[PDB]
Structures are given as structure tokens and as C-alpha cells.
Image (cartoon, rainbow, N blue to C red; front, side, top):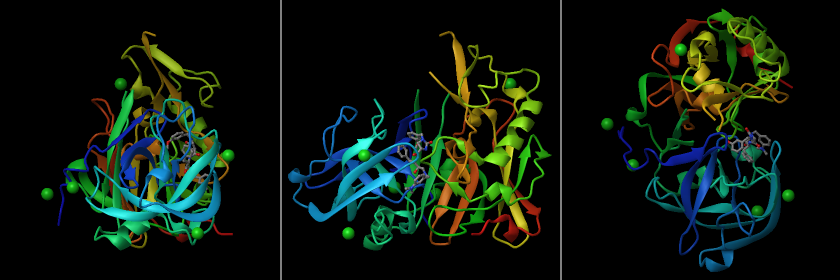
Length: 379
Ligand SMILES: COc1cccc(CN2C[C@@H](C(=O)N[C@@H](Cc3ccccc3)[C@H](O)CNCc3cccc(N(C)C)c3)NC2=O)c1
Ligand SMILES: [Cl-]
Ligand SMILES: [Cl-]
Ligand SMILES: [Cl-]
Ligand SMILES: [Cl-]
Ligand SMILES: [Cl-]
């Protein structure tokens, strides 16, 4: 088995807070575009018409292999939205596996709060499941096509590396790079194939249990989404966590506006008091019954740096109304394997994650845990 994907390592770039993107080409001849890797979506969409924030776009009339599906589509995100027309064309991933597949493409022609100013990406690659793709489930997502058409295993892995202003990382398509992690890989089942839904069974702050019905941890749902920057948490859980994180960091008090992400905090260049902030742990349901494992992040993860003579950051743990979102603040600590064939998601300490001399993120297990099925929410 291949354990070294030399060509795919370091194929991701991005700017802090604006997502990670991979270079792709569409059309004949190939048109190069930077695409946002978003495991919280299932639509492959690219800018397909002029827009001030786009350095370049997809020109359908210049592609021989272009085909119009003669159908429209729009997609509402959390705050940004776009509208386009469906079609298909050949697509590639230069620094990915050497193959060219035909996939569905939403040519974006109208958008709002979508493309960012100077983001450097021009499209979005939703890697989730068909179940949530617009217009409806019959529009086969990109990864699904790539799989049926080539001999690439049904699985991709992601190592997102923060920093402390250009992020990086690698998206290994079809396999697992042993160079990207240390220790062992722990798997949590994928509850349902729509978003990448998992189940959190216990939460800890510097070792101290949050002590809540574990149903509150997955209230609505919990998903791994590289398309979200923060560690979004349900209203009730978010409340408990900030109280705890505040008690733990009490050596220094901060304006209520910090804990709300509204305002950032600063410290003399390189004197950030990391040690005063607690570590955060999430126990995920493991594969064997009554077994769970633990993933732990550091302030370096949830205190996202933001562009003086100081190092400033903003709190990256926000409240959410739609369940828990394990955003980049979570992901950046691990090498995350989206083993789709075996309906599970693996976590391992990331070999690039940002940390100081004394602490490191971690993944430990197993922990004898009972009654985990009831940690999941149902309609
Ligand atoms: C990817 O990192 C980022 C890049 C730019 C901006 C941001 C900030 N915001 C955007 C925001 C947000 O809208 N995130 C979605 C991806 C995205 C990024 C930037 C612009 C537009 C869309 C992500 O897919 C959300 N997943 C849950 C979700 C919500 C609503 C609808 C769906 N569907 C239809 C399946 C799915 N998440 C953020 O954290 C993050
Ligand atoms: Cl090897
Ligand atoms: Cl390779
Ligand atoms: Cl269609
Ligand atoms: Cl729009
Ligand atoms: Cl420190």
C-alpha cells in the first residue's frame, strides 16, 4: 500500500480565516482555478462570469468539452450565496492524482457575500454527500464522480496547517500519507451520509468535564466541516464552555466582547500567555461498542491570529443554532481521514499543527464509555 503521496503533499494554500484551497483545472484546454476545499458542502461551483473579487473565471465558450445541462441552481450558505447554471466538463487536480474526470459544474453567474476581496480562490469544492447537494440529491457531487471513473480509493485525507499570513496544508486524494501524522489513527463512525456527521460523547476543558447530557453536544447535529473556520457550538454548550474557559483563564480578564468574537486581544510581540488558556477535549464515539477516544486542541488552535507591534487574536469558538461544527480550529490540530468506504472519520496528531514548547494537540484512547447511542439527536 502507498503511504507516501509525494505529489499531493503541500497542495493547499489559503489566507487565515479565508479557507484552504487547492489548484484545479476545468475545460479543454485546461482553465486553472483555485478551489476552496469544503467538506461541509456537496456542490462543485466556479466563478463563471466577471466579478471585481475574481482575478479570473471559467469561460464555458472556450471549452470544447463543455456541455450545458440547461438547468439553473442557487445555493444559500451561512451568509454568502451564489446562483449559477449547471453543466459538465473535464476537470483535473494538477497536484492531485493524475487523472481527468467529467463532473457536474455549477457555473456561478450571480452571487452575494460569496467571493471574498483578495481571497485568491475562485470556486468551491463541496466534498460532502449527494444528500445535501442542490438542486437535489440526484446531482452527483465531484468526489463521487472522480471515484467511479478512476481507480482512486473511496477516501481523502486532510491536514490543515494554521500559522502564527498564508496558511498551507495538504489534501491527499485516495489515500493516507504517513508523513502527515504521528501516533495512531482513531476512527469515529460517520452517523449518516449527508454532512460528515459524527457523535461527541463528552467534552472537557483542561481535564474538567462540562457535565451535560451528551445529547446537548450533538443538538441538531455535529459535523466535520473544513468549510467553516470556527468551532461552532450549540447555544447551551457554548455557554457552559465559555464560563469554564473563562474560569480557567481567570489570571487575566477580557472584555465580554472578546468571548463573543466581536473584538480581538493583543500582547507584546511573542509574549502571548498561551499557558493561561486551557486545552479543549472532545470524546468521539469509537468503532468498538462502549469505546470512545479523545481529541485535544490548544489555545493556539482556537485563538485565531488576526492581522502594530503586537500579536493579536480573536476567539474562534462561536455559538451555533444548527449543531456543533468542528471547523478548522478543530481540524488544524489533526490529520483527518475521511474514510468514506468504511463509513468513518479518522483523527491523529498533526505533524504540522502549531503549538509551543510545553503542549501539543493529542488523540488518545480508548476510554470505556457506555450509552453512546443516546448521545445522538433524532427528529
Ligand atoms: C472555508 O473557510 C472559510 C472561507 C471563507 C469564509 C469563512 C467564514 N464562514 C463562512 C461560512 C460558510 O458559509 N461556510 C460554508 C462554505 C463557504 C465558505 C465561504 C463562502 C461561502 C461558503 C460551509 O459549507 C458551511 N457548512 C454548513 C452549511 C451551512 C449552510 C448551508 C449548507 N449547505 C447548503 C450544504 C451547509 N462558514 C464560515 O466559517 C470560512
Ligand atoms: Cl511509505
Ligand atoms: Cl502522489
Ligand atoms: Cl440535472
Ligand atoms: Cl445571488
Ligand atoms: Cl506559554
